[PDB]
Image (cartoon, coloured by chain):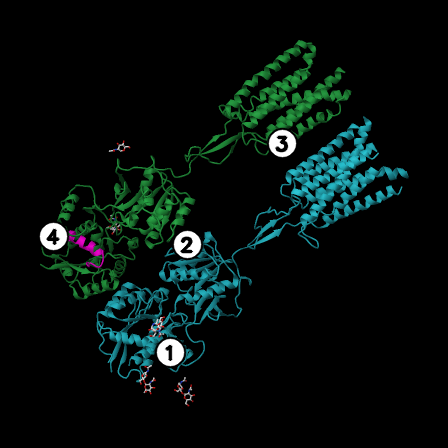
Amino acid sequence: SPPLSIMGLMPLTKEVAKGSIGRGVLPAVELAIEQIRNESLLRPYFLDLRLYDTECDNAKGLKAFYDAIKYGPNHLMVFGGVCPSVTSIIAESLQGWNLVQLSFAATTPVLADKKKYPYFFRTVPSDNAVNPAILKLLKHYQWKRVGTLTQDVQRFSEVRNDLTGVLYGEDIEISDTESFSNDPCTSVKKLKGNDVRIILGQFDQNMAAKVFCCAYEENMYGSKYQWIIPGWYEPSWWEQVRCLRKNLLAAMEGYIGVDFEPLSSKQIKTISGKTPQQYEREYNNKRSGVGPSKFHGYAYDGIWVIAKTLQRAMETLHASSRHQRIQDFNYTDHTLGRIILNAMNETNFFGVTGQVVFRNGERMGTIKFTQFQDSREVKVGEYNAVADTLEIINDTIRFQGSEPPKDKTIILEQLRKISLPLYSILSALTILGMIMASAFLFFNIKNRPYMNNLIILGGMLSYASIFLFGLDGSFVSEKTFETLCTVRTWILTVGYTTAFGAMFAKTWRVHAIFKIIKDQKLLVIVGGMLLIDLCILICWQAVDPLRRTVEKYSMEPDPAGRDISIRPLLEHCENTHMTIWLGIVYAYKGLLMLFGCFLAWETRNSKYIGMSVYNVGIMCIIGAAVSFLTRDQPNVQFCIVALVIIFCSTITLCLVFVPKLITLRT
Amino acid sequence: RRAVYIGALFPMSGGWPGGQACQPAVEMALEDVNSRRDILPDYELKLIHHDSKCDPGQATKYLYELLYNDPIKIILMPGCSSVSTLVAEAARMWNLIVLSYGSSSPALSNRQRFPTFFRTHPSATLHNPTRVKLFEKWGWKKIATIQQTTEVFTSTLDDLEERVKEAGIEITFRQSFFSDPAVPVKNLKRQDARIIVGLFYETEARKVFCEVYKERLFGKKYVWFLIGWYADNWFKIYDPSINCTVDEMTEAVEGHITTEIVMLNPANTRSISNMTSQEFVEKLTKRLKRHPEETGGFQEAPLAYDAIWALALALNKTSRLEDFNYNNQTITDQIYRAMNSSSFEGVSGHVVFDASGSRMAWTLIEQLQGGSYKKIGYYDSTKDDLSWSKTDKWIGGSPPADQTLVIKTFRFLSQKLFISVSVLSSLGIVLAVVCLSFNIYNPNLNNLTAVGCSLALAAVFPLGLDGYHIGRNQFPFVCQARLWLLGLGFSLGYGSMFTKIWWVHTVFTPWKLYATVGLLVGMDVLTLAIWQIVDPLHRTIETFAKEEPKEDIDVSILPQLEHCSSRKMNTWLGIFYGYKGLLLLLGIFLAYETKDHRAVGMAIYNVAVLCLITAPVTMILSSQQDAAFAFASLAIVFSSYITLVVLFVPKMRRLIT
Ligand SMILES: *[C@@H]1O[C@H](CO)[C@@H](O[C@@H]2O[C@H](CO)[C@@H](O)[C@H](O)[C@H]2NC(C)=O)[C@H](O)[C@H]1NC(C)=O
Ligand SMILES: *[C@@H]1O[C@H](CO)[C@@H](O[C@@H]2O[C@H](CO)[C@@H](O)[C@H](O)[C@H]2NC(C)=O)[C@H](O)[C@H]1NC(C)=O
Ligand SMILES: *[C@@H]1O[C@H](CO)[C@@H](O[C@@H]2O[C@H](CO)[C@@H](O)[C@H](O)[C@H]2NC(C)=O)[C@H](O)[C@H]1NC(C)=O
Ligand SMILES: *[C@@H]1O[C@H](CO)[C@@H](O[C@@H]2O[C@H](CO)[C@@H](O)[C@H](O)[C@H]2NC(C)=O)[C@H](O)[C@H]1NC(C)=O
Ligand SMILES: *[C@@H]1O[C@H](CO)[C@@H](O[C@@H]2O[C@H](CO)[C@@H](O)[C@H](O)[C@H]2NC(C)=O)[C@H](O)[C@H]1NC(C)=O
Ligand SMILES: *[C@@H]1O[C@H](CO)[C@@H](O)[C@H](O)[C@H]1NC(C)=O
């Protein structure tokens, strides 16, 4: 039978550790070729394989390739290549004879282009096949803020460049894009300065122990951060290589490892007829000397791929003519290579790794999530991109916290409250001044003429105003009461102007005498400034709505260590452009009060009324002074204005009556 | 004889079609060296050659085609750069020596990876000392760089960074692309840089210039640095891959600086060939039917020429060389030892190459000036000689730079409004002194009030302007002196005014009262001294306006003003205004209380409302151009004028009425 020759280009020596890999993957392909001899898928021909040692030096590999070209027979395919330079160079040069090279360990995305490499295919999942997986894991546990850290190597910068290419369209933020070369410790410094919660590391093996030891020095661990790291190092690599393993182990737990999964968990019949369990058992009892490889699955699948490929392209219309065209290939033909490319590219079937497909020189693989649980890694979850499902292994994951941490700095706000045990004693003092007012009104009607009644009206309105001052502020059970602060401030101002008009018109008439129609003129002169203050009330209504405003005082503390910050807020009734209005109102009050304040110095030789108007004008100006020098704390200002209001509004009646009834009741 | 065969390679097209010119050059060179029997008494030179278009697939096919055939070749000649690296990497397995002629990779200077490799072409790092001197001439600091993603450009950009870092010039915007110019020219428009250096081949130079015309990023503040060994017609060849027309590109590429290096003797000398450079160039223009402005590789053909002549003299230095096989090494080491000590004088001057390379002395620099290139000057790096010719036109003459800023001082109105203020103060002084002399020459509290109002009319002038007299920057001293004098003057005048109405209110209801009111006046100088002890003076700077109000020049105008202040002066001046307002309202109440007295009360009623209406309008104002100083001076001089012209009306009018 005429043989169909094919050539494998593998490192077979002992001077390189990848010779162990080639010697490990040789039993799977010889078992596969003996299975092909068992089934005998091809009556007239028989397959032949010629092995060639490379050691992946470029000159020696091209020399062995040239020797095989010059001296060997009419080869049909070429197979293999592990070292990236001699794969890159052969994949660029392959079109000079229009042939196809099949690899199984080239794990660099630079072979993704087909204008550069139209004849190249691979079955190993690349490093860009973890990027849908990490998005699905993040949406599985709702993470928002992340900081990246990429080592300045071409591969890490390439996957960093592809993070942006895969990240487009979702609610994701990338804050700290630090890219160091050999000092990761200042990078952890910068990361702690931007205090980002989740690390997505990209570096080599030797940098990792130094990064975690001087991240212990920054204390970048705890129940606050996660670390997503590519975990393809050798197991227990950290046992050999300024920082002790005692000061490393209590911070090297919880580090999420992102690998590719070798096998599956299906016990289903493949096209071989066996299960992955039977295949692995037969493999490990096939061999005994070699250290176990982890690529023999891809070697076994790809041999059956190309065998099914050559039988489906062998089926041509040309029974005779193609059989001569294969038997007389002088390396020049390209139409046969085009049909072989079409029949190989449309390969889709189920093997040991699963249902294999091909999306542009790539097979859709299985991504193995893992976690370093208790001094070792454990498999925790899978993800299949052909179906886009992310399996997880419940009852296996653990957390040093209790919830997968929240990522942004989350805040909460509330109003500034006042001391209720301070407010309650003032609410108890509310009633006594009012009852004394309504009792001395009955003493005045027992005397029964309008002057002390107007004084009592001002006192009652003041005792109502000082009650409803802070009753609307902190207790916000009446929510739309900031519109009514002006509707009670006009009540307060009317009581104020009534009391001070009864203080002022009497002393002005005492100055003018120092007739009953003159008392009528005095009453209408008080009514004139009453209506002047009513016009100022409607001018305050027209000048601003005085609506509900909120001052948001932002300091964001934490009383009990939780990251839910607190920010207080204060209700403000003003509209911040009535400063001219309140300034002219306070000047109006000062001009109305300084007349009597100056005149009390003169007429001292209405005997204690000037001493009353002085001893209330000082308290009123100290109330305005402490009013403008506060609202930093809305409790002390309100209690001090309640204190001065219950001072003045009953001290006027007390110093106007304390000798009156004492001399009338001797 | 003996036909000795030499393999060769000529890229006829692709990114650099130099082999179109070098092939007749080497044909001429082989016919000229096929003349002397003293160099080769026994052999005969033969040439085998192909094309590769700087394509490694064809290059690998042609290397196999020459290697695995007949007859045996000895020396190879690779054209492009990546293919030159590949053949110098793989020449060791046949024990061969390789000679390149166009590569510029400075990493190709290593002898470990490349023991059997030489190159006549000098590297790309001799654009950087000339680049940093042309940057040092104009002091520009914000430069942006853009490159195609290649090793032969990143080793240049790394040499330029590690050369510019000692000069203290930062490189801010460092971008890169591969074949998409849209997003990086979007980023350059969004980063609005001034001077831009680019490193890419021609077909994308046309694409990036279509993109920069489309983004409208050419123009006034944009300087483009490119290499200059392109042809002069390059923006004229029809390329249907882009829809841009020829003259908007021609207007866009106008006025940019290009750099290169020399390739041959600028003088006229004679080689061993007994010809010169100029006659050689004449012979190339004779035999080449195309134009030198349209062909490729025309400037570099003499390095190929002296490369053959050098190897020919090396072969004469070796002088039984007919049994060469790729396995042995003795012939190769003997020829290598003879070629190592190669040092002579050829058409390009002294030809030494078994050193660290870069043996050229002068470089060259041009500028597109109106549809044609034109020379700026010459240079040498060792002697640091920058030969000039002063032909650089610019946008109207000046070189556009990065960005500047102007600090503008906020001008006063030292004009007729100030001169009117000064003349009203002088008129008040003269009127006051004339009325006081008339009163003395015919009310001692009235004389003291006249002295105080004269001191106010003497302190009215020295409010200053925006730095206009002999000697400045003592503005706190002169303003604090004027303020102290005006304070004491107003204190004296108002105290001697108010003490009369105080005593008339006392008499309504000899030097005791006068001496106690004089000490009441001198209390204010104790307040002035307490203001002088803890924080007397300060000349602060306000930056009240926004930067860059200018319309055409990119120098941001920041207007800054100055007012005399202190450490904490606001509450102090508020307290002093409150104290003086207290005294003034006391006077205005006593004038209605104890109603000389009628005129004194009416003068008090005028001066009080004047001072109270102008305290706030000088307290809360800051635009001193026509409001603050104008209102204050109008207030003070109208006060003193009207108060004097009312208080001395009844004296002199009724003395002779
Ligand atoms: C490999 O798979 C198919 C095999 O033909 C190709 O993609 C097909 O292209 C044809 C023609 O353009 C379309 O009609 C089909 O719809 C495509 N898809 C499929 C599934 O057949 C192409 O050769 C390769 N495609 C990929 C994605 O690698
Ligand atoms: C290059 O130019 C061609 C022709 O001008 C463009 O194709 C369109 O051609 C039709 C022909 O009827 C015109 O009506 C359209 O106006 C053309 N489109 C435009 C945008 O000009 C082609 O689009 C141009 N290339 C690009 C990139 O715009
Ligand atoms: C170049 O060749 C010429 C002749 O082939 C050389 O000699 C010339 O000889 C004549 C004989 O009388 C003299 O008159 C000329 O002055 C010579 N030319 C010179 C000196 O340039 C000549 O020496 C050769 N070499 C050079 C460098 O020109
Ligand atoms: C080039 O070849 C010549 C062979 O003719 C070498 O030697 C010559 O030797 C004779 C006899 O002594 C002298 O008269 C000539 O002057 C020599 N030629 C030259 C050019 O000097 C000569 O040594 C060889 N040159 C080199 C550099 O190898
Ligand atoms: C080829 O050139 C000369 C001649 O054989 C030698 O040059 C030596 O170069 C090294 C490198 O720096 C120096 O340290 C030696 O002093 C040089 N020796 C000399 C000039 O005699 C050497 O054999 C070769 N290599 C180089 C680089 O020159
Ligand atoms: C899976 O997780 C849920 C929720 O925690 C739990 O109730 C259930 O028992 C888990 N299943 C197994 C098999 O542990």
2 or 3: mark nearer the eye: 3
Q: Are marks 3 and 1 in contact (CB under 8 Å)?
A: no
For mark 1, give the secondary structure: strand
Nearest to N terminus: mark 2 or mark 1: 2
In the image, the chain rendered in green is A
Residue B259 % position (x, y): 45, 66
Q: Is mark 1 within 8 Å of ligand 4?
A: no
Q: Chain of mark 2?
A: B
Q: Is mark 3 within 8 Å of ligand 2?
A: no
Q: Is mark 4 within 8 Å of ligand 1?
A: no
Q: Which residue is mark 4?
A: A34
Where residue A581 is drawn, which disc sits there?
3
- Residue flagged by tag 3: what amino acid is it? Trp
Front residue of this view, candidates A318 and A230? A230
Q: Is residue A26 magenta?
A: yes
- Residue flagged by tag 1: what amino acid is it? Phe
Q: Which residue is found at the position 63% from the left and 17% from the top? A: A457
| CA distance for labels 4 and 2 | 56 Å
Q: Which residue is mark 2?
A: B184
**Left or right of B400 in this view: A511:** right
Nearest to N terminus: mark 4 or mark 3: 4
Range of the magenta residues? A12-31
Check chain identity for marks 3 and 1: say if they share one.
Answer: no
Front residue of this view, candidates B6 and A265? A265
Q: Is residue A522 above or below residue B421?
A: above
Q: Which residue is mark 1?
A: B344
Q: Which residue is found at the position 62% from the left and 26% from the top? A: A537
